[PDB]
Image (cartoon, helix red, strand yellow):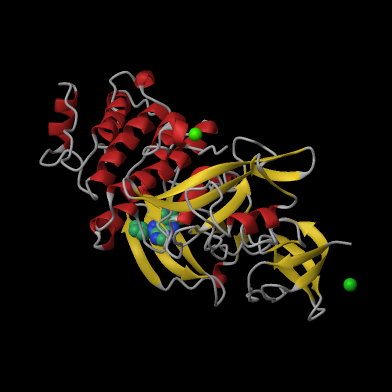
């Protein structure tokens, strides 16, 4: 006997799936992935539902101010998104204290601008929870209600929970390999050598992006290999691989990033009013993605702003990764002269990418042809520092551009530095007595 409750209003797009609203409760019949067979209680109909739209009744996630599986940096990114003001808060699972919680509040001090402060949450005895040992609480709800009524030792009082967005709907069940007939490629987005990229529609609803491949050099059954491999590498900073069309020419169906490529975005009009901290935030998201790739020991072989895509909410993801196991200004000398290409050469690439982002999509090594570049690189030449670039960010680029491959940093260290670029290590969690 398992009863859940819906967190957002949902509409049926498939045939055997249910429809509900924010607040309606449902019985659970089957657990099998992101889709659960469930019986509604208001309609009493039995349909399939997205498992990330519901949560077990009165089990924390039911509350508006609780956010599961969110990191400290992520909570910082969300609380500064449009729709949030001073005091906009949230409670999340602790990232450094597994089995504990943390409170994140939006504040403003004049000498830095808008900020997000994080307080730890202690829990034992067990009489309840506390942030300051003087004021103790039984449940997290009453705890919230106290600090909501006057800032008892905080840099700001609590106003409203974070402006949570409705999650992206999960892919259709059993729909890995799909009939091509399900597609309506209604706009060409890009074309180049090996294939095209279209904005498409999968069955009337659900927008989608399709990459069509003109065959030849790329084989046939040598593609269900890389497909089934990259399908196992799910990540929030990598572009999601949804479906793949069986018959040749093979179609690759992925999520549709609403604002195209990063290079197009930076060169664009909106992506030029984007301040420096947001660019650093972008490169931190990319670093996070390259760090996940690094943990899995894989290589990208082609890293640049053109291969980074942007969602409508300014989220960066990584596109056709590993398609070099399936154009040199971003390439390290070890991979140019000797064809090395490792995770370290990708660190070099990330250095040039970092150069693109800061220069609003400018061409690396401007005024230089590829020969003029390669001849100068052996001469020990590195790109100068832009007039709007911090010396510390420049030092990161320089570290990425070491002659020795293994003297270069890791994407784990690069991400960490970039994530807390404006925050001293001691300032991460403000501790109040
Ligand atoms: N997913 C997308 N969403 C929105 N726009 C996209 C894309 C892609 C794209 C990039 N890499 C991909 N690899 C497999 C599918 C796939 C699709 N390419 N593009 C266009 C290509 C250049 C600017 C935008
Ligand atoms: Ca502190
Ligand atoms: Cl029942």
Q: Position of residue 26 (x, y in %)?
A: 79, 70
Q: Residue 69 appears at what percent x and percent y?
A: 62, 48
Q: Residue at coordinates 19% horizontally, 26% vertically from top-left?
A: 377
Percent x, y of residue 57: 77, 62
Question: Relative to residue 222, is residue 319 drawn left or right?
Answer: left
Q: Nearer the viewer, residue 158 or 12?
A: 158
Looking at the image, can residue 245 be seen? no
Q: Is residue 189 left or right of residue 70?
A: left
Which quarter holds ligand 3? bottom right
**The C terminus - image quarter:** top right
Residue nearer the viewer, 382 or 116: 116
Using the image as rendered, state which of residue 69 and residue 143 is in the foreground.
Answer: 143
| Outermost residue toward the left in this view | 367
**Quadrant showing the N terminus:** bottom right
Asked whether, in this view, residue 391 is left or right of residue 36, the answer is: left
Residue at (66, 64) in percent of width and height:
53
Residue 105 visible in the snapshot: yes
Name the residue rendered at 63%, 62% in the picture.
Answer: 64
Examine the image and state in which quarter residue 374 appears.
Answer: top left
């Amino acid at each position: 006997r398992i009863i859940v409750v819906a967190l957002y209003d949902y509409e049926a797009i498939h045939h055997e799936d249910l429809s509900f609203q924010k607040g309606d409760q449902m019985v659970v019949l089957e657990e099998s992935g992101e889709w659960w067979k469930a019986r509604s209680l208001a309609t009493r109909k039995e349909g399939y539902i997205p498992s990330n739209y519901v949560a077990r009744v009165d089990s924390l996630e039911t509350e508006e101010w609780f956010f599961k599986g969110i990191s400290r940096k992520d909570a910082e990114r969300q609380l500064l998104a449009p729709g949030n003001m001073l005091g906009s808060f949230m409670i999340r699972d602790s990232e450094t204290t597994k089995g504990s919680y943390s409170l994140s509040v939006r504040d403003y001090d004049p000498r830095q601008g808008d900020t997000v402060k994080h307080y730890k949450i202690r829990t034992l005895d067990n009489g309840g929870f506390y942030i300051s040992p003087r004021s103790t609480f039984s449940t997290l709800q009453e705890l919230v209600d106290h600090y909501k009524k006057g800032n008892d030792g905080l840099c700001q009082k609590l106003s409203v929970p974070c402006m949570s967005s409705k999650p992206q709907k999960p892919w259709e069940k059993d729909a890995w390999e799909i009939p091509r007939e399900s597609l309506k490629l209604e706009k060409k987005l890009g074309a180049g050598q090996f294939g095209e990229v279209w904005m498409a529609t999968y069955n009337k609803h659900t927008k989608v992006a399709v990459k069509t491949m003109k065959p030849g050099s790329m084989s046939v059954e040598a593609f269900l290999a890389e497909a089934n491999v990259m399908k196992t590498l799910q990540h929030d900073k990598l572009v999601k691989l949804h479906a793949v069309v069986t018959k040749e020419p093979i179609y690759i169906i992925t999520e549709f990033m609403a604002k195209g490529s990063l290079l197009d975005f930076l060169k664009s009009d909106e992506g030029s009013k984007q301040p420096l901290p947001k660019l650093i935030d972008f490169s931190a998201q990319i670093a996070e993605g390259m760090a996940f790739i690094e943990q899995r020991n894989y290589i990208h072989r082609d890293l640049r702003a053109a291969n980074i895509l942007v969602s409508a909410s300014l989220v960066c993801k990584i596109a056709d990764f590993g398609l070099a196991r399936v154009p040199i200004k971003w390439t390290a000398p070890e991979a140019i002269n000797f064809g090395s290409f490792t995770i370290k050469s990708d660190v070099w690439s990330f250095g040039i990418l970092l150069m693109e982002i800061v220069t609003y999509g400018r061409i690396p090594y401007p005024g230089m042809s590829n020969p003029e570049v390669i001849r100068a690189l052996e001469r020990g030449y590195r790109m100068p520092r832009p007039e709007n670039c911090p010396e510390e960010l420049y030092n990161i680029m320089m570290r990425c551009w070491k002659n020795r491959p293994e003297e270069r940093p890791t994407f784990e260290y690069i991400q960490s530095v970039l994530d807390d670029f404006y925050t001293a290590t001691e300032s991460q969690y403000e501790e109040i007595p």
